[PDB]
Structures are given as C-alpha cells and as structure tokens.
Image (tube, coloured by chain):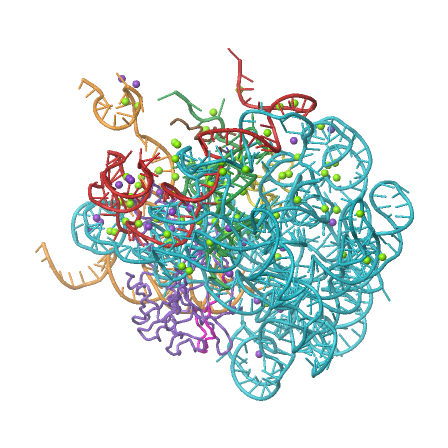
Chain colours: A brown, B yellow, C purple, D orange, E red, F cyan, G green
Amino acid sequence: VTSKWFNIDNKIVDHFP
Amino acid sequence: MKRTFQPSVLKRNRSHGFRARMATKNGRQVLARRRAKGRARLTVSK
Amino acid sequence: AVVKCKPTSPGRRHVVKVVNPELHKGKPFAPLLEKNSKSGGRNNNGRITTRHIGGGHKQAYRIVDFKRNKDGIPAVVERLEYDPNRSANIALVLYKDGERRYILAPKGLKAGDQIQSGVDAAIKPGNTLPMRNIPVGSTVHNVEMKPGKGGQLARSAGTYVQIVARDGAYVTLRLRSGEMRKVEADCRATLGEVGNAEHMLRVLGKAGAARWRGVRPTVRGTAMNPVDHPHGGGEGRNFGKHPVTPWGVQTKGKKTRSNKRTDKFIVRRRS
RNA sequence: UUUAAUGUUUGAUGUUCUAACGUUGACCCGUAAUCCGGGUUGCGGACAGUGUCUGGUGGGUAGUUUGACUGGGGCGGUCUC
RNA sequence: UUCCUUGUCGGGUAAGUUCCGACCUGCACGAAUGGCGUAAUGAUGGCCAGGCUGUCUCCACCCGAGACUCAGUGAAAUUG
RNA sequence: CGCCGGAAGACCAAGGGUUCCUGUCCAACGUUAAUCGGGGCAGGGUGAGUCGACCCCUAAGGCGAGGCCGAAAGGCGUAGUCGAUGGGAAACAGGUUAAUAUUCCUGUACUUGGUGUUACUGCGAAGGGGGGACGGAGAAGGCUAUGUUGGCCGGGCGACGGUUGUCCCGGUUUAAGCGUGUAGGCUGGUUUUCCAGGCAAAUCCGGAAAAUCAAGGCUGAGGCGUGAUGACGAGGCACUACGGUGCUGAAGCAACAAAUGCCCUGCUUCCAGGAAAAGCCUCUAAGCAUCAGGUAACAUCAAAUCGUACCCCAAACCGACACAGGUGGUCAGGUAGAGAAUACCAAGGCGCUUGAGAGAACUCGGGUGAAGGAACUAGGCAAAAUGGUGCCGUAACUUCGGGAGAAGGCACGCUGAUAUGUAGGUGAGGUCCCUCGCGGAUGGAGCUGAAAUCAGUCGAAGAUACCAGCUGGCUGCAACUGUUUAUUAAAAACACAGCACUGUGCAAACACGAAAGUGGACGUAUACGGUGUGACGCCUGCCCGGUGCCGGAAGGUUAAUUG
RNA sequence: GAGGACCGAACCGACUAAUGUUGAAAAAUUAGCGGAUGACUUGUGGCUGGGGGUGAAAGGCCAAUCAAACCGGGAGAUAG
Ligand SMILES: N[C@@H](Cc1c[nH]c2ccccc12)C(=O)O
Ligand SMILES: [K+]
Ligand SMILES: [K+]
Ligand SMILES: [K+]
Ligand SMILES: [K+]
Ligand SMILES: [K+]
Ligand SMILES: [K+]
Ligand SMILES: [K+]
Ligand SMILES: [K+]
Ligand SMILES: [K+]
Ligand SMILES: [K+]
Ligand SMILES: [K+]
Ligand SMILES: [K+]
Ligand SMILES: [K+]
Ligand SMILES: [K+]
Ligand SMILES: [K+]
Ligand SMILES: [K+]
Ligand SMILES: [K+]
Ligand SMILES: [K+]
Ligand SMILES: [K+]
Ligand SMILES: [K+]
Ligand SMILES: [K+]
Ligand SMILES: [K+]
Ligand SMILES: [K+]
Ligand SMILES: [K+]
Ligand SMILES: [K+]
Ligand SMILES: [K+]
Ligand SMILES: [K+]
Ligand SMILES: [K+]
Ligand SMILES: [K+]
Ligand SMILES: [K+]
Ligand SMILES: [Mg+2]
Ligand SMILES: [Mg+2]
Ligand SMILES: [Mg+2]
Ligand SMILES: [Mg+2]
Ligand SMILES: [Mg+2]
Ligand SMILES: [Mg+2]
Ligand SMILES: [Mg+2]
Ligand SMILES: [Mg+2]
Ligand SMILES: [Mg+2]
Ligand SMILES: [Mg+2]
Ligand SMILES: [Mg+2]
Ligand SMILES: [Mg+2]
Ligand SMILES: [Mg+2]
Ligand SMILES: [Mg+2]
Ligand SMILES: [Mg+2]
Ligand SMILES: [Mg+2]
Ligand SMILES: [Mg+2]
Ligand SMILES: [Mg+2]
Ligand SMILES: [Mg+2]
Ligand SMILES: [Mg+2]
Ligand SMILES: [Mg+2]
Ligand SMILES: [Mg+2]
Ligand SMILES: [Mg+2]
Ligand SMILES: [Mg+2]
Ligand SMILES: [Mg+2]
Ligand SMILES: [Mg+2]
Ligand SMILES: [Mg+2]
Ligand SMILES: [Mg+2]
Ligand SMILES: [Mg+2]
Ligand SMILES: [Mg+2]
Ligand SMILES: [Mg+2]
Ligand SMILES: [Mg+2]
Ligand SMILES: [Mg+2]
Ligand SMILES: [Mg+2]
Ligand SMILES: [Mg+2]
Ligand SMILES: [Mg+2]
Ligand SMILES: [Mg+2]
Ligand SMILES: [Mg+2]
Ligand SMILES: [Mg+2]
Ligand SMILES: [Mg+2]
Ligand SMILES: [Mg+2]
Ligand SMILES: [Mg+2]
Ligand SMILES: [Mg+2]
Ligand SMILES: [Mg+2]
Ligand SMILES: [Mg+2]
Ligand SMILES: [Mg+2]
Ligand SMILES: [Mg+2]
Ligand SMILES: [Mg+2]
Ligand SMILES: [Mg+2]
Ligand SMILES: [Mg+2]
Ligand SMILES: [Mg+2]
Ligand SMILES: [Mg+2]
Ligand SMILES: [Mg+2]
Ligand SMILES: [Mg+2]
Ligand SMILES: [Mg+2]
Ligand SMILES: [Mg+2]
Ligand SMILES: [Mg+2]
Ligand SMILES: [Mg+2]
Ligand SMILES: [Mg+2]
Ligand SMILES: [Mg+2]
Ligand SMILES: [Mg+2]
Ligand SMILES: [Mg+2]
Ligand SMILES: [Mg+2]
Ligand SMILES: [Mg+2]
Ligand SMILES: [Mg+2]
Ligand SMILES: [Mg+2]
Ligand SMILES: [Mg+2]
Ligand SMILES: [Mg+2]
Ligand SMILES: [Mg+2]
Ligand SMILES: [Mg+2]
Ligand SMILES: [Mg+2]
Ligand SMILES: [Mg+2]
Ligand SMILES: [Mg+2]
Ligand SMILES: [Mg+2]
Ligand SMILES: [Mg+2]
Ligand SMILES: [Mg+2]
C-alpha cells in the first residue's frame, strides 16, 4: 500500500527541486 | 524467500503458553482480561 | 625462540611466532582441569558490560596453585606445559608424597628441578618463603598482598618485583609499573622472575589471529553518528572536540583512581 | 598594652590505642553448600563508608526558546519621538 | 585539493575540456583528524593499444512465445 | 513420442492433521469441460520388551526453600530442581493388506529387571579413584558397500543383406545373531615391603624401593564357519471377476576395479591447546554380622503408557492462491569425464488443469549475415571472441614468496606394429619351510592396464558436441583476505595486523544495576580499558598565546555552619 | 604437507544487463559474476526490551513497521 512504487520512488516523485 | 513466521510448537508454548503466562504477575493480568472479555481460547495451548 | 614465517601469502608476511621446543606435546593432567565457559562480556543482566569480547577457541581451566602452602615437603618438576588462560607457562610438580600440582613456571626452571616452600626453604628460584626471610634486593614473583590469600602480583610472563626495603612489619616493593608499595612482611613470594619472557616479541600477523583469542573488532568513535558516540558526526572527517569515552568522561590524561582506604600503602605512584 | 605560669575545655595539628565500624584474609560450625549467618583469630580503624545539608563541575540526560516588516524568503536596513 | 582555467610546455591522435610527463603563479597541500613512496591484491576510478565483433554505417531473413480470429471462463485503475 | 534422473526419484526430522484407501455424487471449489480430484457424502484404515518419545544423566540457560537486597510490585542467588541440539540395554531377513508394518505372520535372535531353588562367599555410600571423555589439518595402509568382465544356468536363431557363434536377451540373492580371531593400534608384565597424598578409611588410585621375567594384556575392520537340506529365484504351467490369484522352480561362482563408508575417538603434525554428569568398573566408612547382602547356574514372570495413516524441495509446511520463492538430514547405478561439473540413459517418476487456428505491424527469447570494423555511446553497455591436457618459452619491477596460466608457440582422431596387451598393478595352482596356521618363501597362470614412438589412413576441420581464462601498456585510491546501507549506494567507506598516547596496584579502572550483586577475570601491568592512526619503507619539523588536562599553593574572592 | 594460498561444483552471497512493474513474485527469473578450510556456513535450544537492546558503523536491524517498535489507555490531546 502507499505504493504504487512509483509514488515512493523519489526520482520519479521528487522531480522539481 | 524466508518469511517471518517459522513455526515450532516448543517455542510457541514456552513463550505464550498457559504455564508461561501464569509464571509472572503481568502474565496473570493478561489471563484475567481474556476471561473478562470471554475468550474461548485463553492461550495458545494445543 | 622467535621465528619469522616466510611470506608465502599476504597473511603470513608479518607473523612472528615464539616456539618453545620443551613444552609438553600431550594432553594435560586431567584431575586438575575444570570447565570454563565464555561470556561474551555479558553480566547477569544479559547486557554487554565489556566491549570487544566474544568468540575464540574453547579452553579448559587449569587449577594453578597460587598459595603454595604445602610447607616443608620437596617437589620435583615433572614437565612444562602450555596454559591457554595466561601468558606464562605452568609446570607440573610432584611432591615426595605423591601429590601433583600446577605452579607458574619461573625463568630457568626445567624438568627435574627441586622446589620447596616454607620458612626453611633455600634461596633459589622457584622456592616460596615469607618475605621477611627473603633478603632485601631480591627479585621475587607471585607476591601475596594479604597473608595466606595467594599470589596476586607479578603473575604475567616476564614480570617480577624487587624488595627495596624492610621496616618492622612491612616491606617496600617496586612493582613492575614502577610504583612503590608496602605489604606486610608475612606475605609469601616466589624467588625469581616469571618465564616465557619472549611472549611480547610475537606478532599476530593477521586480523583472524586476534579473533582466535576472543577479541572482536573495535569501531572508532569518530566514525559513528552523534547519537552513538560523543565523537560522531560531520561531513568528511571532523573532530573539533576533546577526546572522551563513549560515556562522556575525558580520556587522555584525567586520573580515575579514587580509593581512600588503600592510599596508606602507596609510597609513590608510578610516573 | 605586651608577656607568661596556672586548671579547663575547645579548636587546630600530630602521634599512639581499641571497643564502634570495615574485611571480596585464615580457620571452625549450621552443612551434603566458594550464598548467607554465627564463632575463634589476623589486618585495618575512628579513617573509610552511608544519611541530611552545602559550594563546585556537569549536552551524560531532559524541557524549551531562537521577533516582525519585506514587490517570495534569507543577507542588508528599519521598528519610539 | 586549482576559482581564474580547456594555465603553459612536452607526449600520444588527422583532430585530445579527459589521460600521461613536467613547470610552480599552492584562490584554498603538508607531516599519526599522519606526509611521501610502494611489490602483491581489488565484481575499485581514469586513459590507451591488439584481437573480436549487428554497437554502428544500415539493416535483411529465419526459428519459437505473445499480439490477431474461433470456442470456454472472465478482471482493474478511472468516471459531474 | 517427449522431459527429469546428486532429481522433477526414494526415506525421515520440523510443520500440518485425515489430505491416506474404498463406494458414491458433480450444485459450489478446480483460473476451461469433467464421467476426474488433495472437492461433497458415507464407510474403512495407524497393532512394538528391541524404532521414537516417556525414562536415567547432564550443557547453555531457567526457576529457586532458607538468604542478601529493594517505597510496594519485586531483583539476585545457595542448597536443590528442571532444561537436548549431546551421554545411557537389547532384532534381523523373508512373507503379507486397498490402505500398517524392523509393530502382524514364518524362521532365527538378543537385553534388562523381579521372584524362587541350589552352590560358594564380606556385603555396605550422599564419600575416594578409574572410565565415560571429546581440537584443526594431513597422509596413507587394510577392507567392504558397489560395479564391470568372464564362467554357469534358462531362453533365442530374427519383418530387410548377414547372424550355430569371438552371436543375442535375462538371472547368478541371501540378514541379525552365534563361533574363530586377522591387517592394524596402544601398552612392559608379575610379586613383595614401605609412605607427610586422594576433606576420614582403604586391599583401590598416586608415590618410593627390591627381585624376577621377555613376554603378557587391552582393542580391532574385514574374511571364514554356521544361521541356511531354509528362504528368494528367470521362467514355465493353470485360472482370471482381466486387476491379479494358485502351483513349481534351474544356476546361484570366480577374477578385477573401488569409495566422500569402516578399522579410525587410530597415526603424524600444528597451535588458536580442543564439554559436563550419569550408566559402568573398583575401594573402603558408619552399619550388619549362622542374617542381610554379593557371585554363578537354572526355572519362572514382567517389559507398562503415548506416536505410528498420509505429504515432507511440497497442490498437504512458511509465503492471503492448487503462487516460477523459502525449507534441516540420509540414500547416490551405467557410458564418457578429474569430478556430486556436463552430455545421454537406468530404477523410478512425470508432460507443469484452457484449447484450436492463422502465420501482419510491434514486443519478448534466439540463429545467421556481404564490405567495413567502435565510425556507436556518457562509457566497447550488450554481444562476439578466448577457453582443455602435455611440452617448449616467458619482461619490467620486487617486500625475493612473487609477477606468471605473463606474453607466445607446438602436438592431439582412427588403424597397425614395437607388444597376438608393453611398463605398472593384482596374484591362483604348484613346490619347500616351519609356526600346521586368517602363516612364510618361490613361482608365475589368469585378470587389469596407461604413456610413448614408428608406419598408414579419413575429413574443410581430431581440445570436434556439452563443458571451458580475452590479452597487454600508463596511472589515482585503499597494503592485503574480510564487512556494510534485508528491499536503488559494495566503495576510496567500516574492520584489520602494526603504532602511539593515556588511564588502571586489584574490593583495579570501567560498564549494567535506588541496592545486593554481576561482567572485567577464576585475569594481575609482557595484564586490562579508552582514544586516535592504520601492513611495509623513508620519516613525523616550529608554536603552550586560546580551550582542555596535569602539578602547585603563597595571596585575593568564596557555602552550609556560628551568631 | 603449511596457507584468513590457487582453480572450481554443493553451500553462502549479490557485481552487470535484459525481462517484470494492476508481476509467476509486496524484491523474483534468465545469462554471466564473487567467496568457496575459514574473521566460513548451517540445525536445534537459549540470552539481551524501547531513550532501551544489538551494530567489522549504513542512523543499519529489533516480525513486510524504526532520527525512537507494537498494543491498550490519558483521549473526543490541540489545531488562529
Ligand atoms: N520496481 C520494483 C522494485 C521496487 C519494489 N518496491 C519499491 C519501492 C520503491 C521503488 C522501487 C521499488 C518492483 O516493483 O518490484
Ligand atoms: K571424573
Ligand atoms: K578501530
Ligand atoms: K564523518
Ligand atoms: K575482626
Ligand atoms: K567519611
Ligand atoms: K515580485
Ligand atoms: K512593499
Ligand atoms: K586547494
Ligand atoms: K599535442
Ligand atoms: K602532436
Ligand atoms: K599511500
Ligand atoms: K573492489
Ligand atoms: K588500478
Ligand atoms: K464441475
Ligand atoms: K485459481
Ligand atoms: K536428544
Ligand atoms: K561409587
Ligand atoms: K600401587
Ligand atoms: K507406521
Ligand atoms: K579456464
Ligand atoms: K565488493
Ligand atoms: K561502512
Ligand atoms: K594500552
Ligand atoms: K570469573
Ligand atoms: K598554545
Ligand atoms: K595551554
Ligand atoms: K601555560
Ligand atoms: K594441501
Ligand atoms: K555452531
Ligand atoms: K520509544
Ligand atoms: Mg576494547
Ligand atoms: Mg586497535
Ligand atoms: Mg557514517
Ligand atoms: Mg552527544
Ligand atoms: Mg572537510
Ligand atoms: Mg537538548
Ligand atoms: Mg545547560
Ligand atoms: Mg510542553
Ligand atoms: Mg517574515
Ligand atoms: Mg526581498
Ligand atoms: Mg596538449
Ligand atoms: Mg599531471
Ligand atoms: Mg588534508
Ligand atoms: Mg589542514
Ligand atoms: Mg606533528
Ligand atoms: Mg595532526
Ligand atoms: Mg602518497
Ligand atoms: Mg486476439
Ligand atoms: Mg474470446
Ligand atoms: Mg474515484
Ligand atoms: Mg533426457
Ligand atoms: Mg476432509
Ligand atoms: Mg486419494
Ligand atoms: Mg467448472
Ligand atoms: Mg490427489
Ligand atoms: Mg476427497
Ligand atoms: Mg534466581
Ligand atoms: Mg534431571
Ligand atoms: Mg503406505
Ligand atoms: Mg566419580
Ligand atoms: Mg533350459
Ligand atoms: Mg545357452
Ligand atoms: Mg533375412
Ligand atoms: Mg549375458
Ligand atoms: Mg547427577
Ligand atoms: Mg501451504
Ligand atoms: Mg491475511
Ligand atoms: Mg497449476
Ligand atoms: Mg511452489
Ligand atoms: Mg538448501
Ligand atoms: Mg547435472
Ligand atoms: Mg523408468
Ligand atoms: Mg513470428
Ligand atoms: Mg557482417
Ligand atoms: Mg556463407
Ligand atoms: Mg565477413
Ligand atoms: Mg567515438
Ligand atoms: Mg558520435
Ligand atoms: Mg560486458
Ligand atoms: Mg614489457
Ligand atoms: Mg619463479
Ligand atoms: Mg621469474
Ligand atoms: Mg600460458
Ligand atoms: Mg587524477
Ligand atoms: Mg580494500
Ligand atoms: Mg574483497
Ligand atoms: Mg541496497
Ligand atoms: Mg542498483
Ligand atoms: Mg547493490
Ligand atoms: Mg583500550
Ligand atoms: Mg583513517
Ligand atoms: Mg587545577
Ligand atoms: Mg582461499
Ligand atoms: Mg561459484
Ligand atoms: Mg549481506
Ligand atoms: Mg545480480
Ligand atoms: Mg543466477
Ligand atoms: Mg575469478
Ligand atoms: Mg573458487
Ligand atoms: Mg576460523
Ligand atoms: Mg548520514
Ligand atoms: Mg504491521
Ligand atoms: Mg523490518
Ligand atoms: Mg520521542
Ligand atoms: Mg486530558
Ligand atoms: Mg480529534
């Protein structure tokens, strides 16, 4: 749960710093 | 791969059995709560 | 003798071993053995109370005679043996009445030599007397601190004590640390130094050689995180603080002795 | 005003002592027991150690604080008359 | 570890911001939070050559498993 | 027909618990249908003196009368008492059910107790001594399981050329026990006299002295004999309710090869120096002494209770699933091979619970490719290549070991001869000795059998398949083998041997605990703790002003207390 | 006949790439890769408990949960 591993993977998720 | 539950009835009883609950003051608190609630199986015994 | 191994492997290049051809090649004397289980540095609470201890080889305790209270009966050294529990070597001695015991082997002692204990014993290495019968200046070992209690000083390989002075009921000894101390003159001591004096010339050579002796690896405090040691933290290698033990007390210089009841026996602390 | 001699503490210091207290010294008994207790003796001894009070030290541990305005915030400047 | 900076000079390439050798103008190395070397070792970092090749010029054909049609069973995210 | 065969076969422990076997049913369950099923329903099935548990004995550890300690609850711990993953008596072969079998049946065995009779007699423990009783590696020697070939026995004479022979197919098995005592291994034997030792005693163990003897003893695989004129046995015959059931039954030998099993808890060596207690043997104490008790033979009785089906690399256990995952031990055939690798097979077991077509793009997994050959790309990523045995040959540098399998190169099939099968291994009959035996010497039948050389011969290719290093040059970092972010980081990070500083004199410092206590350590400064650095080589310069630590104590300031 | 020696299966690991990403699988498969007599690996049992343990040190691990586990309570915490 929470995943959807691509909603945890932070290259995919944290794309705009 | 290896999971977390590896059964063994010796350690199941030496940890959670009736005679292990009765051996300490807090173990006898657990048994008193399960009797008050009304549980059919008090402990993991047989 | 010390011998250097040849470098036929990276783990043999730096090994130096001490080989004594005159130790016993056989099983030890069974009646004087006991069981010695390890601890891992854990007390009766199950907690680690000394770090870097754990593993090693199985060992059997040899009941060594530190009191030497079999007075007046001569003994003959039967053999020299290996003891895993101490750095020195033990000897097996046979008394004229048929009793066998283990004693710490002094320097120069070999199979066939005669030893004796008591007030009438001769002044030769291996003999045990009260220290009021030992001439001043002598080099003694296996010294008692309280009469009749058994030897506690100068028990490690190559160590000894010097009787510096005698005054009434006390003698002044110079301990191996270079520290003067007064003991009662009715305490016993064995004449001579402890053997195996080349024990310090050995080189373990590899990291597994110290795991054979029951010593687990040490992690530097400066390589931890701040929650673990007071030295931890930082990007790159940072120290910027005074060295301390993992429980916060200052090391490198601070003095920890506080014993006011045995301070009367210290003539002079070491330097 | 100074001084001593006098008897006393009462303090301070020092040296002896033993009887409190310590003993993870030896021996004996309960006892079939390296716990404990009692006994005999040795060594220390009014010290050590513990309670109450007290000065110091104390990120070892804990609870918290670390302003606003602002052509985004920080940096700088300002904040009342 | 050097910002200026692809410093300059030499080597290697037809051509080399990387690599190797030097120089010293060290923004901002340096001596047990060690300095400088070092044989052997490393699923360690950089660079060069030989062999080898569908990596590529630049793709073509073939062999199987799906994709497609028939019968049977039969989901899911999502949705004013 | 295909697949596994160091398993995808067989047997267990753990775990599960009726999934086991028979009859019947097909609603739901089964990724489809189902007449089938580990599904529904009903019935049946688990047989022990010897296997396991229970039992006797202990390890780590637990609990713990008194005790010590703590506001209470409680903590620790002595005597004790539990606790196996370890020590302790005893059974094998064949037969049989649909389903159990070392449990039932047939044959042949063995163990420990009680009771009784007879004979002789010093018995007796909570105590003493022995024993149990113990590491890593290495090297063999002697064997066996097992396999292969030959002989023997039974059958065969071949769908298509040939096949009465140097031919083909199948079998050639037998245990525990009991008797003997061998290859090997260890040890000197016997008797007497004395003794500060073994908490007391001792005739036992330990020690001392003398005489005498050159042998004795302990242990020990295998073989042989018996067990066994038995059982089993290829087939044949007779029935079949077609699955099976009944009867009879030949030969049942030798040579060679050979274990990772056994002798072997041995032997040799090394350092890191390698459980405990009981069962067992023995010695006495108090005690008892026409007894009791002990030894032996015989007879008799007893050996209770619980497990036992079935699955166990799995559709039955752990993963929500009939889930490409995980799961300890035992067994271990053939042909090639060094091999438990790899290829093809045996015993045995399976084809993985949707199929049928077609033969588009694209995706996945593979094969081949003209000329070129890294031009691709962040980067030779990925692929291709190399790859075996024997011999020749091999640089810088080096800590003298290495580097190094450096690099590179040559030979390799089959047939014949040397030699009707050699060198080597094994070793019968026979002859002689004596020790008349599980012996020694000689001898060489038979069996097995590399490597090489010469000569010939086939292909494009002889390490033919599977299997099986790419290599070299310069350089940074870390000496090295290790460890690490289970599940995006394996590294230059952590560790490390070595080095230094520092604390610690033993009721040690130090750590866990209101404490008692415990670890450090049954250790003692050549030891122990902390800190930093990190093999080895050459080395490690100046600053004590700041912060810290160590020493000092004169003077200044300074708490409770006093008043 | 030594060795934290060498090559290499079982065994223990996890260096690369492709597949998969509502998977066959809440971390695997395929092909290669490392160690493989040791600071090894594994079975059965035991001990350490939450500001605590353990850690060849990564804030790693403590039942698919970790810069402070899980369960119940204070508790209907508080929320400009
Ligand atoms: N994507 C992979 C790996 C993965 C598992 N859990 C993840 C969480 C986050 C990122 C990746 C993963 C998978 O699904 O198997
Ligand atoms: K014993
Ligand atoms: K360290
Ligand atoms: K750091
Ligand atoms: K006293
Ligand atoms: K005091
Ligand atoms: K703006
Ligand atoms: K504004
Ligand atoms: K710099
Ligand atoms: K150039
Ligand atoms: K040029
Ligand atoms: K270096
Ligand atoms: K590496
Ligand atoms: K390199
Ligand atoms: K059906
Ligand atoms: K299903
Ligand atoms: K057992
Ligand atoms: K006895
Ligand atoms: K004797
Ligand atoms: K059964
Ligand atoms: K190779
Ligand atoms: K690695
Ligand atoms: K690390
Ligand atoms: K030290
Ligand atoms: K101890
Ligand atoms: K200074
Ligand atoms: K200073
Ligand atoms: K100063
Ligand atoms: K070897
Ligand atoms: K183990
Ligand atoms: K917590
Ligand atoms: Mg340490
Ligand atoms: Mg160290
Ligand atoms: Mg870190
Ligand atoms: Mg801190
Ligand atoms: Mg820095
Ligand atoms: Mg704070
Ligand atoms: Mg503060
Ligand atoms: Mg608050
Ligand atoms: Mg603001
Ligand atoms: Mg602004
Ligand atoms: Mg240039
Ligand atoms: Mg350069
Ligand atoms: Mg630096
Ligand atoms: Mg600096
Ligand atoms: Mg310096
Ligand atoms: Mg420095
Ligand atoms: Mg350097
Ligand atoms: Mg379709
Ligand atoms: Mg359809
Ligand atoms: Mg929605
Ligand atoms: Mg096959
Ligand atoms: Mg059922
Ligand atoms: Mg069935
Ligand atoms: Mg159906
Ligand atoms: Mg079935
Ligand atoms: Mg059924
Ligand atoms: Mg207790
Ligand atoms: Mg018991
Ligand atoms: Mg069956
Ligand atoms: Mg005994
Ligand atoms: Mg015939
Ligand atoms: Mg015939
Ligand atoms: Mg014909
Ligand atoms: Mg035949
Ligand atoms: Mg006992
Ligand atoms: Mg299951
Ligand atoms: Mg569930
Ligand atoms: Mg299936
Ligand atoms: Mg499965
Ligand atoms: Mg396995
Ligand atoms: Mg195979
Ligand atoms: Mg078959
Ligand atoms: Mg196709
Ligand atoms: Mg081409
Ligand atoms: Mg062609
Ligand atoms: Mg070509
Ligand atoms: Mg290019
Ligand atoms: Mg390009
Ligand atoms: Mg590659
Ligand atoms: Mg060269
Ligand atoms: Mg050489
Ligand atoms: Mg050379
Ligand atoms: Mg070569
Ligand atoms: Mg560089
Ligand atoms: Mg390294
Ligand atoms: Mg490594
Ligand atoms: Mg990771
Ligand atoms: Mg990755
Ligand atoms: Mg990784
Ligand atoms: Mg230390
Ligand atoms: Mg370092
Ligand atoms: Mg000071
Ligand atoms: Mg190795
Ligand atoms: Mg491997
Ligand atoms: Mg790992
Ligand atoms: Mg991988
Ligand atoms: Mg793999
Ligand atoms: Mg390799
Ligand atoms: Mg290997
Ligand atoms: Mg080891
Ligand atoms: Mg961090
Ligand atoms: Mg959870
Ligand atoms: Mg977890
Ligand atoms: Mg918190
Ligand atoms: Mg409230
Ligand atoms: Mg609320």
Image quarter of the N terminus of chain B: top right
**How far across and down, in percent of the image, does residue F317 sit?**
64, 41
Is residue C240 inside the magenta stretch?
no
- Residue B35 sits above or below residue C74 on the image: above
Quarter where residue F2 is shown: top right
**How far across and down, in percent of the image, does residue F348 sit?**
72, 46
Image quarter of the C terminus of chain B: top right
Q: Is residue F459 left or right of residue C19?
A: right
Residue shown at 41% from the left, 76% from the top = C118
**How far across and down, in percent of the image, does residue F384 sit?**
50, 41
- Residue B37 sits above or below residue F252 on the image: above
Return the residue nearer the eye: G5 or B35. G5
Number of callouts = 0
Quadrant in which ligand 23 is drawn: top left
Q: Is residue F85 left or right of residue C118?
A: right
- Residue F206 sits above or below residue F316 on the image: below
Is residue C65 inside the magenta stretch?
yes
Return the residue nearer the eye: F205 or F189. F189
**How far across and down, in percent of the image, does residue C16 sit?**
39, 63
Residue shown at 40% from the left, 67% from the top = C151
Return the residue nearer the eye: C50 or B27. C50
Q: Which residues are magenta?
A: C59-81
Can residue C120 be seen in this snapshot?
Answer: yes
Q: Is residue F546 left or right of residue G53?
A: left
